[PDB]
Image: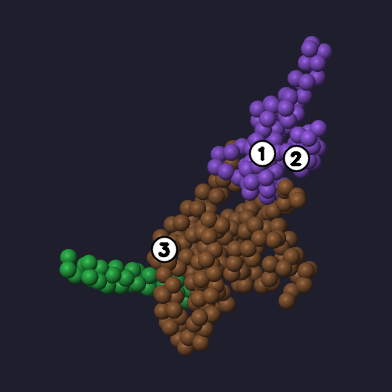
Amino acid sequence: EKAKSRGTFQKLREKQQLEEDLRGYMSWITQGEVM
Amino acid sequence: QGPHMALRKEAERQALAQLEKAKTKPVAFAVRTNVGYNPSPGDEVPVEGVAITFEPKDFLHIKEKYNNDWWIGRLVKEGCEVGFIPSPVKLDSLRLLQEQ
Amino acid sequence: VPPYDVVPSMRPIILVGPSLKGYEVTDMMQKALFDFLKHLFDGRISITRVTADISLARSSLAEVQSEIERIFELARTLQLVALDADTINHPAQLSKTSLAPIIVYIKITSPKVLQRLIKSRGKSQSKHLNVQIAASEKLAQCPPEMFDIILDENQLEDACEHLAEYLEAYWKATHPPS
């Protein structure tokens, strides 16, 4: 509780969202290169 | 009365046969609506019951032209059939009767 | 004020504004989406490549209207129309003509990811950092209900589960059963 209310929730939410938005960004590339 | 029902009821079935014979006809031209409209009892509707309604910003795939006051076409919506589209001169006729 | 406007019988499918077009970022993002709708709806679509600016009714009136009437020809056989328009970056950019196309809005859910995609394109697109984020913001400033189809999905299949099913709900709206 001392961690999550301080700042540690947004460290694991952003980087899990910034990874799943990265693979979506890189899927928009890897189909554009093949087709 | 009896002399008025010989021609008025033989026009409803003749306009119903034209309405049934236009559903299989291909789509000629589609329009974009700007205002809203629903069918009323005094709108001189040729087949009383088979008219369609549109609100602002709707689409109407018009099949054919029945007369100078009603078009025949369908609503762009799941399951909707053909219907009586009021012409722009019919939409010009309906508003001026609200003043007179 | 005319109440009825002569629009095509089958609306042309078009997506614009995720990132300003005319770049390696936004166009290669859309080029993956044109590949999905080519073979999924093969035989019931007409996909074209648009050159002249159709937001004008630069090019004259005749070179644009002869391409607008080509869209009018592609609505006659009652099939889907798709446009690869390269300058469309606004909802009201295509609000004055008599086409009314389908506004598929690709939604980048996070603005910080775009400039990380920008640094993935080398240093060619790294010279064009803030200029893409202008209409990326302005399309994000436009209301989403003014659009038609919104794609906020990172993976291929989840943006394409909306991109196939929405027009399949739209095809059955245009075409009645016998």
Look at the image and give the colour of chain B: purple
- Whether residue C7 sits left or right of residue B100 in the image: it is left
Please give the count of numbered marks on the rendered protein.
Answer: 3
Residue in front for this viewpoint, C163 or C79: C163
Name chain C's colour.
brown
Q: Amino acid at mark 1?
A: Tyr
Residue identifier under label 3: C153
Q: Which mark is residue B37?
A: 1
Estimate how packed mark 3 is, as few (under 14), some (14 to 19) or many (20 or more) residues with alpha carbons within 10 Å. many
Label 1 with label 3: CB-CB less than 8 Å: no
Structural distance between the alpha carbons of marks 1 and 2: 9 Å
Query: Mark 1 falls on what kind of element?
Result: loop
Residue C128 can be seen, yes or no = yes
- The reply to whether discs 1 and 2 touch (Cβ–Cβ < 8 Å) is yes
Give the chain of mark 1: B
Residue B73: % across, % down: 68, 40
- Crowding around mark 2 (Cα neighbors within 10 Å: few <14, some 14 to 19, many 20+) is some
Give the chain coloured green: A
Are the residues under badges 2 and 3 in a single subunit?
no
According to the picture, the residue beneath numbered tag 2 turns out to be B91
**Dot 1 alpha-carbon crowd within 10 angstroms: few under 14, some 14 to 19, many 20 or more:** some
Q: Nearer the viewer, residue C125 or C48?
A: C125
Which label belongs to residue C103? none
Could you tell me how far apart the alpha carbons at marks 1 and 3 are, in whole angstroms? Answer: 38 Å
User: Residue at image x 50%, y 76%?
Assistant: C133
Within the image, what quadrant is residue B83 found in?
Answer: top right
Amino acid type indicated by mark 3: Glu
